[PDB]
Length: 269
Ligand SMILES: Cc1nn(-c2ccnc(Nc3ccc4c(c3)c(C)c(C)n4C)n2)cc1CN1CC(O)C1
Figure (tube, helix red, strand yellow):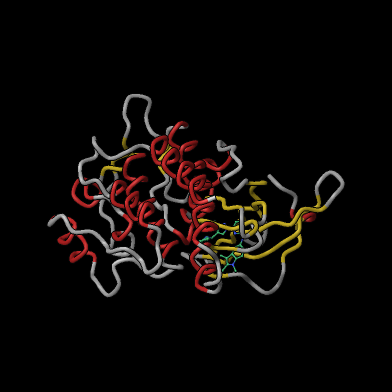
């Protein structure tokens, strides 16, 4: 566990989630001080603590340039998950506020995400919340995946995790087998990645605007998909549609997705 006396938190906050705050902080290391982001658990007054610790347990096992690194867990006034700071914050919000960012730049960023998800797939972890809000920018040209609170280490003898009843909020990023069978796999992360790309090339607009989850589900069952974002490169829209392959077996893994991106990034460059 980290030493609370070595951590300073900034009084102003970055955002409030479900349910807690994220604050910027500074953690004194063996000699330099490191800038951190700290997820702080709201707990006016048990098992919310367990959730944060599980989240920490996953991040501890992950080591990759395109995933947020955990520094550690701190037990103090509140329970806290201390991470290396990605200064520019969430990809969706950054693109909302930086429409000047060019298609080539967006391609670079989503490609980096595919590289981190290839690693995750190889480590047999499912993310289960892969969306533009959970990609963070270190700089305008370097993205990392964040938010492992829903993530699961897959059993040695299976390539999916079985959940129970989901609410409405996450539906727009879920593959059909998630909606209907509560089955989560690297292939379901690939589906969510297609939505993440549609988000990124829409400069952080919401997918399926104005539709209820039930309507999204119906649309997908009819073979319909979101249309091409204004200005979006045709080949990136083509890749989105491949990620939205209905049948889990025929949908690509992250190896294949990463190759298509690398190749198109090269073409554009
Ligand atoms: C688990 C978690 N880590 N984490 C984090 C990790 C490393 N760096 C950062 N940097 C950062 C920088 C600026 C930020 C943010 C995060 C956030 C959430 C906002 C609103 N800004 C301006 N955040 C943010 C979160 C909360 N998730 C981001 C999703 O949007 C909710």
